[PDB]
Each structure stands twice: as structure tokens, then as C-alpha cells.
Amino acid sequence: SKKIAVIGECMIELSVKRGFGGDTLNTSVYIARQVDPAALTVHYVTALGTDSFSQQMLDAWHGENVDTSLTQRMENRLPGLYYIETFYYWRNEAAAKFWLASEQSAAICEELANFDYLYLSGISLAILSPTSREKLLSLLRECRAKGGKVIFDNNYRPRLWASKEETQQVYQQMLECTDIAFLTLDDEDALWGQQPVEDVIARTHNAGVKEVVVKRGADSCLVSIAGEALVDVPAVKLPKEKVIDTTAAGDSFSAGYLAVRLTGGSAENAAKRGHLTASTVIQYRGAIIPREAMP
Amino acid sequence: SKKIAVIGECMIELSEDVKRGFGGDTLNTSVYIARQVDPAALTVHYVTALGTDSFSQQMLDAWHGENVDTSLTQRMENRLPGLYYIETERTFYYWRNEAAAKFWLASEQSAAICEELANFDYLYLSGISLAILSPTSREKLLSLLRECRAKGGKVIFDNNYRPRLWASKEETQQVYQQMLECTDIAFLTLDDEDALWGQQPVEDVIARTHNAGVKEVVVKRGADSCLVSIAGEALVDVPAVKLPKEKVIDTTAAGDSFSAGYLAVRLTGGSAENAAKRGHLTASTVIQYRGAIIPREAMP
């Protein structure tokens, strides 16, 4: 079997109902829902507190067959919290920010260096200190040196960074450590200024990235593999009335794409699955849709 | 009319069905004073800082609806209110460490708001109001209190002690000592004094507090009687009217509502004894309801 570790943060979510939500955790759940665990196991890597909100999260994740054995619990921290009306965040002291700055960080990183795949988003980098970002980048390099592959989702939240220049510098270091990049085009527009998709693709290959997957909302997905012709796969047009909530469209697309791509499927079939997944998700309220209990 | 400014923090409150409201020790007190005084005799001003968000807005409107004036409360672009979460036997969870309220003395309106406050008849704050401020901000506040008193204002302190908000017991001790050297009326919850300074006879709690300079010491003893000691005068000792224990639903806000009831009377010409009676009456009613702020209709 192969193993993927998904690194980032999941918060307490308020919308009045209470759940949980985080871009990378959403992605982890959709991968786990779609793969044969004999082919690929999904590990979420974060930190939480020893409180009962953290517990309820861990429990639900185990119910989704997401392995949390590399997630840490920190006695004097809580999860971050966000509220949906507009988003409001109470996340600047989250346990998740500190997973690379504890006494257990080292052993966890030695375990992760041996993983087949490591995945993280722009948010996963944003929440780390400059020093923790360095440690994470070194882990990625070590994993790749051992034959592992690094996947990055460019999910861009300017409010989490000190400046546009800081994000650019950190994304540049990240792309130089990346094998597969998921780039939401609007996010590349926002971060780097508006540029033709061909230049977005080119500069990303120039950073060293072999496989660049460009997500374009309702426009088609472009997959560019260095030295190969472009793959162009249209989305699953739904009538307007079936679209209820576009939250997690992007995160679930990355999930569907990897469920296929990391179990032997073509880039075209991986894109088809990303589109099918995102299309399903947007027809139900909430980031995480009801599990298919009986397929 | 006289003006009292009440200074501290009100947070976004979640309680779990899951409901959203707002709560904070000094805000609860402000609301309870505002519910019981003649606006011609005494106006109530809450002094804090909030966000520009709609949570801050729902708070401001709600307080306006209670006749609390918010003109000296700041709205901060890049900050949100603190937020807390109650799970119900209750557990409390906090996300309060970047709340706007922490920074009201570190802004560009700070000096000018303080200039208005220096001229007020009464300034009131609690130990929580002090805990959330940086050392530098605490010093400016203490400076404001001195200026106010030199102008003939009176300073009122509620010792509400929350050790989680402080760096150390030593730090709390130092800042309380400084506060009490600047205080005219001190509401001392006796369990808080025991926790902060070690268990000592109530007579010594009273004496040391007079010794620090405080003229009127009001000791809250939960179900036990209220003791009011005014320097140079015999002790005043006022029991609550006994309440059947099954009617006690939620002791939340008991102490904050007692201070409010006391001040609604004491600051409008009433005796220490009637002020204590109204403290007890207010607290008695309050604890018979779920939530810090009971319904207007429920009031004494």
C-alpha cells in the first residue's frame, strides 16, 4: 500500500450550528472516501488541543478512515475557530500553527520523510512561523530525496500573510520543492497579477514542478506535464438550481484528482474525477457532504 | 446628571442547540446599573473597543437598547471582539487574546478619550479590565485614575480575579496593590481575596484595603452576608433574603449584578445598607435565570 500525509489546519466551524472545517482536512476526507485503503492510506498531520472539540474532530476523522496517528495533542492550546455569517477567524493561537515547534516534531518528520506523498496548501504555509516554514521546506526536500512526491495546492488567503511579497517568496521556495501543483487560477491572478494561463504554467514548470494542474472554476481544467502536450478537460455543467454552496469546490477537486492520479490513473481521468467530485459537493450545504453510506 | 464610565471587555458568547449572544463582567454590571437608575440622576457609559464587524454592531445596538451610552467605545478596523464558548455543568473556552478591548489605551483616540474620562464623576473597572491590558496600557489607565480623582471623580474597583488571564500571582498582586492605592470604593469578592492573597480573616481583608487608602470596602460573601466598611465608621452587615436552592439556575453574573445593584443605590444618594440590600435583591433575581443578562421584564 502507498501512504499520503496531508498537512495543515482544521478549525472549529460555526455557521447556529457547530462543526469543523479546514481546506486540507476537506481534501483528506474526500481522498479517503474515494480510495481503496489497500492502495492508499490517508494521514492528517496537524496539532489540536486535549479538549473535547479536538476529540470530536479526531473521532469524526477516524470515522472517515483518516489516520491521525501523526497529529499531536497540546494540553495548553485549543483549535482555531471560524464563524460563517463572510468569514471571521479566531485562529492566531491555534495548536495547528505549532506542530513543527514541539519535542515530538523531530520524530514526526523522520516518519514523514519516508512517506510516498506529502500534500499541503498555501494556508498550511501561512499559519507557520518563518522558522517552521523552513523546517517544513527541509522535510519536503528530504522526502523527495528519498523518492517521495510533494503536492501543493496554492489556496491563497492574503489576510493570513504579512504582505504580498512574503507570500510570493514563500510560494517560490515551495514550488521549487513541489512535484504536482494545483493552481486555482484566480488565486494566481490575485497573488502574481493577471497573466495568461500559458505563463502561469510556464513559470511553474520553470520552478521545477513536473505536473501543473490549473483549476479554473467553471472553465476547463488544464493539466500540463513537462515535455507533454496540454491536457484540457471540461467541467460537468449543472443547471443553476442544483448549485447550493460553492464552498470546498476547489479542495474536493484536488481530492478527486489525487484519488485517481495516485492510484495509477491518467491525468485526463484524474481531472474528470476532480470535476465529478466538485460537482457533487456544490449540490449540498457544507464543505463536507453526507458520506455515501451505501453506494 | 452624574456620569459613570464602566471600563473593560465584552465578548461574543456562544452557548450549547447552540445560541449566540454577548457577555462580559463589566458590561453585565453596566446593563444592570442602566436598568435601575434615573437617567436624569446617572448616565451609564461603557468604555471598550470593538471591531467594525457586524458582531460588534449587534453588541452596540443591544447596549443602546439598554440605555448604555457607547460614545467612548472605539471601533477597530483590523480587530474582532474576543469570543468565548460555554458547553453545558459548564465548561468555558476562550479566544480572547487579540480582542479589540485589549488595545483601547494603545490607539490614536486613547489620549482624547482619557481626557473625557478624567472629567467623569465615577470610573469603574474590574480585575479583568486590568488583566487584559499590557503593562504600558495599565500604567496609562492608573494615570487616568489619579487625574480623575484629583478632579474629584471617584474610582470603583471590583476585584473579580481570573488567574488564567495573568502571567503570575505575583503580577496580579502588584497590579491590585497599585489599583487599590487609586480606589475609592472596592467591591471585594471574599473567595477572590483568599485565592489571590491567601486565606485571611475578613477583618484583615477590610483593614489592609483601608490601609491602601480605600474609603469604602464592600465585601461580597456569596450566600453569606455583605459587609460594608467605611473608614471611621462601624461595620454594616447585610444578609441576602434566603432563596430556595432549586430556584438557583445559574450563578453566572451574580457578583457583577450585585455590584450594579449596590451602585444604582449608592451613587444616587442611598445608604450603604440600602445599597447592599439592592445588591442582594439584584443578584437574587439574576441567578434564577439562565444567562448573564436576564430579560428586562424579569427585573426586581
Image (cartoon, coloured by chain):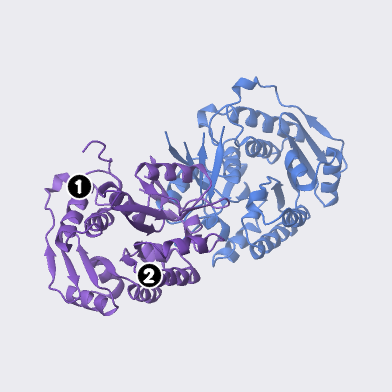
Chain colours: A purple, B blue
Q: Is residue A137 visible?
A: yes
On the image, the x and y values in percent for residue B220 come to 73, 36
For disc 1, the marked residue is A280
| Image: A184 above or below B297 | below
- Gap between marks 1 and 2 measured at Cα: 37 Å
Q: Residue at x 18, y 73 (%)?
A: A197
- Is disc 2 on the same chain as disc 1? yes
Q: Residues within 10 Å of mark 2 (few under 14, many from 20)?
A: few
Q: Is residue A254 left or right of residue B25?
A: left
Q: Chain of mark 2?
A: A
Callout 2, which amino acid?
Answer: Lys
Q: Which residue is mark 2?
A: A146
Tell me if residue A86 can be seen.
Answer: no
Nearest to the eye among marks 1 and 2: give it: 2
For residue A151, the mark is none
Viewport quadrant of the C terminus of chain B? top right
The residue at the far bottom in this view is A206
